[PDB]
Structure formats: C-alpha cells, structure tokens
Image (cartoon, rainbow, N blue to C red):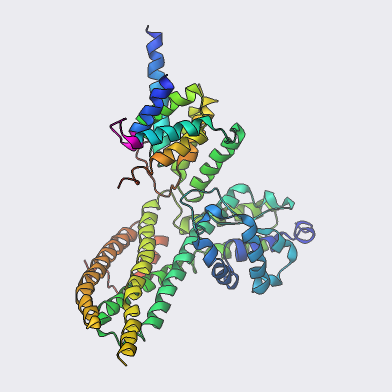
Amino acid sequence: LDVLNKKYSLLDHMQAMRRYLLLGQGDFIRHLMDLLKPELVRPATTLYQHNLTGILETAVRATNAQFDSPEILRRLDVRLLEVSPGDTGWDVFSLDYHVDGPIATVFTRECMSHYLRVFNFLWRAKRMEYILTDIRKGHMCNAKLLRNMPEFSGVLHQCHILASEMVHFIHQMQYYITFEVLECSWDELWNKVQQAQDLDHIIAAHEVFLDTIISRCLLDSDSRALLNQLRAVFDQIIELQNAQDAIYRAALEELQRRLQFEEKKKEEENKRIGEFKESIPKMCSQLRILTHFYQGIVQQFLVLLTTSSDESLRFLSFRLDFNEHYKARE
Amino acid sequence: AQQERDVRELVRGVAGLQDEADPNFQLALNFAWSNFRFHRFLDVNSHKIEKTIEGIYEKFVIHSDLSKAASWKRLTEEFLNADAHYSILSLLLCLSDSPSNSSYVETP
Amino acid sequence: AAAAAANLNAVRETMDVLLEISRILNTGLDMETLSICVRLCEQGINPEALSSVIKELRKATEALK
C-alpha cells in the first residue's frame, strides 16, 4: 500500500476522480458549461473532438482545476459517443478519465461505467438548471421595460409565478444531489480508504461507494418510473424557455415601432393596440393550462415518492414538501 | 425482373403513390435508376458494423436503459446465427436513429 | 414439401426478429417494406443506395403536403 500511494499516487486519483469526473468541483464546471453553451446547443452531427479539446484547455487553465498536478490533469480528457441524425451536443458528450497506471485493478471498468452513468445524469440536470436561471434573468431584465406596455401585465405576472414553482423544485432536488448523494458516500469511502490495511479492503470500500451512489440517485431499474416523471419535469423547462420569449419577440418590438410612429408624426398603432386585445387571452389560457398540467404531474410524483424506498427516498419528501402545499392541492 | 418489381413496390409503398402514369412516379423511378447505376458508395466492413452495434449497446447502457440494452444485444446476436446479415443490419442502422424513448413493449 | 415449409416458418421467425430490430431503432420501415429490401439485397445492392432513396421518397410526402 505504501509503494502504491507514493510511487503512483493512488489517492490523488480518487481526489481527482470526485472533483472532476463526478463533477465534485463546480467552479470548473460552470465555466466549462458556459464556454460549451453555443457549441453544444448546436446539433452534434457536425461535432468532432478537436473543437472540444482546445476550448477545454482554456477552461482548465483559467479555473481552479489548474492547481492540481499535470499528470491527473493530463489523464482527464473529453470523449464523445456515437452520433445520430437527431443528435445535439447536450445529448452526446462525455468526460473520459483514461487510466495509464496499474490502478485499473482498484478502478475497474464496471465502476467506470458507473461513473459514466452518474455523470450523464448529473450533466442533464445541470444543463436544465442553467436554462432555468436564464429564464429568471430574462424575467429580471425584460420586465422593467414592459412597464410601459400595460396590457401584458396579466400574462407576464403569471409567468413569474410558474418560474417560482420550478425554481423551488430545481433548488431542492439540487440540494438532495448536494447532500447525502455525494456526501455520505464520500464519507464512507473516505474513512475506509484512509484507515485501510489491505488492498482488498480498499477495493471493497470502492464497491459499496459505487453501489450507494447508484441507489441514492435515480439510476435503478426500479426507480425508472420516477425517472420518467423527472424527465417530464425537464421537458417543461425548455417549453417555458420557448413561450416566455414567444411573448417578448412580439411584445417588446411593438414599443420601438410605436416610437417610430411618434417620430414619423413629428391610426396604425390603433390597430396594433387592437391586435393585443385578441392576442393576450389565448396566450394567457395557454399558460393557464400549462400550469395546471405541470402542477398535476408533480403531485403524482410526490405521492408515489412517499412509499418507494423506506428511508432514503422518504427524506426527499420532507425537503420537497416543506410547506405541505402538496396534499393540500389534492 | 423481380428487382424491377421491387423498385416499383418500394417507390409505391413509401411514397404512397397509386399510379405509374403519375409523372412524379416517373421522376422518382428515374432517380432510383440513376442512384443504382452510379456507385460512389463505400463498401461495408463487418467489424465496423460490430463496433457500431456495441456502441449502440453502450449508449443504451449509459442512459440507464439496461433492459433494452440486454434485449438489443440478445436479439442482434440471435439474428447473426443461422454477409447478407451484415448488409441488412447496416441498412437498418443507417436508416434512422434518434432513440431517446423506449419504443418497445415486446419481450416475448 | 414438408421440410420446405418449415423453412418458410423459419424465415418468418427471423423476419419478426428483424421486425423488432426495426421497431426499437424507431425506423419508418414496417415488415412489408423490410420484405422488399431483403429481396433487393438478395439480388445485391448497396444499403447506402437504399437508405438514400428511402430518405428521398420520405421527403416526397413532404413535396406534396
């Protein structure tokens, strides 16, 4: 054990296996996803790895991740999966830690597959969260100009509400991903490696760490129904991303058009006002039925969540139902 | 002979045309004949197919769709028992892929 | 004959196997279209060619829509 952890630095591999591959650092990750916004939103059929590596280098040199050893930093590189004609960059992307040491015996390929699965799960949710933060920023920026357009104030307020429903759910789930999911498991592994008297005990401690993080995340073949419910929650985020700007891309343009009419005058805007009295109600009702739909499905998620697993999954319900606003809806 | 009937059947079937005095039928058939008689395609290699199949199996595994991966692996290995196998497989692979949904109800 | 019809059973078996393989890749193909292209590849043809023509004719329901 002495020669393995000094001549090859076995423990540094674990420390960099959480921080980077399991997305344990996130100074690195938010800047990484920021630089990878315009590239990965573009469809990934024309994506090749050489465009990923070069921007990856700038991202790793700029952020905190720079300060660790160049060896383990060198052993971090991107990889992609196979392409589709429906492919987009957030769907197909991977970080791949390639092993150049004899450490493969303690970091076997099955647990590397486990790393891959937990990473993909934690990639999709971090994308949709930033979409939601974009929505909130758009709310906080556009709305101080739409104070001079009085008629949208209904629907614009109503959007404000639905965002708060998502912002709650996306800030509590992402706290359950913070604690007990990357923290009890890390404590277990961190105790049972730092004491260890046998390589076999190191390996068997690695095993249960992977099993616990598979169970606490929704990656079982039994929590698949809960996962489908969660995917339906990820859907409505990009739906709202569409509809919120579908307001603005007609709304806010008219005000500049109205100023142009005023600069002309130094009857047509009457028609522009008249079209709003038709446009507003159907968009409002669209938002209404969307709100009903979303609030309907999330309650069904929670009521299933109460009796799925005895302790672990039950703890999610207390955090996610703090106000007891749910079961007071049904 | 039967090949020409196959081209007729294919054009009729997927285009939904019911007439061959249809000029658009005539243009599509001429397109097919120009397509067949010009060869600029790459020839198929079986090991590259096998690499593609295991890659699809991997992508099924990564998305936590493990049962679909097991069935897909089992069915493809079962199909490759008892050349033309590979060509049909390559066709089926290349034709379409966007799979993010289950699209399955059968494990009989 | 009798052994000559158990072969017809056996190709029906494989083509339902290929039918599931078609359905879980989410292709536009059904069993009947598949039954045509197997005959084409029995005569011998590039699948690169046939995928191109199918990707063309599926856009011919879009050229009349």
Asked if residue A219 is positioned above or below residue A287 in the image, the reply reads above
Query: Looking at the rendering, which quadrant does residue A4 occupy?
Result: bottom right
Between A122 and B29, the one lying in front of the other is B29
Q: Position of residue A196 (x, y in %)?
A: 68, 59
Residue A164 appears in view: no
Residue numbers of the magenta segment: B13-24
Q: Identify which residue is drawn at 26% across, 85% down.
A: A150
Q: Identify which residue is drawn at 24% across, 79% down.
A: A272
Asked if residue A184 is positioned above or below residue C33 in the image, the reply reads below
Q: Identify which residue is drawn at 50% across, 34% down.
A: C49
Asked if residue A101 is positioned above or below residue B68 in the image, the reply reads below
Q: Quadrant of the N terminus of chain B?
A: top left
Q: Position of residue B107 (x, y in %)?
A: 38, 35
Q: Position of residue C42 (x, y in %)?
A: 48, 22
Question: What is the residue that sits farthest to the top in this orientation?
Answer: C1
Q: Quadrant of the C terminus of chain B?
A: top left
Between A322 and A51, the one lying in front of the other is A51
Residue A266 appears in view: yes
Between A64 and A277, the one lying in front of the other is A277
Q: Position of residue A156 (x, y in %)?
A: 29, 78
Between B22 and A278, the one lying in front of the other is B22
Asked if residue C48 is positioned above or below residue A69 in the image, the reply reads above
Along the horizontal axis of the image, is A276 left or right of B42? left
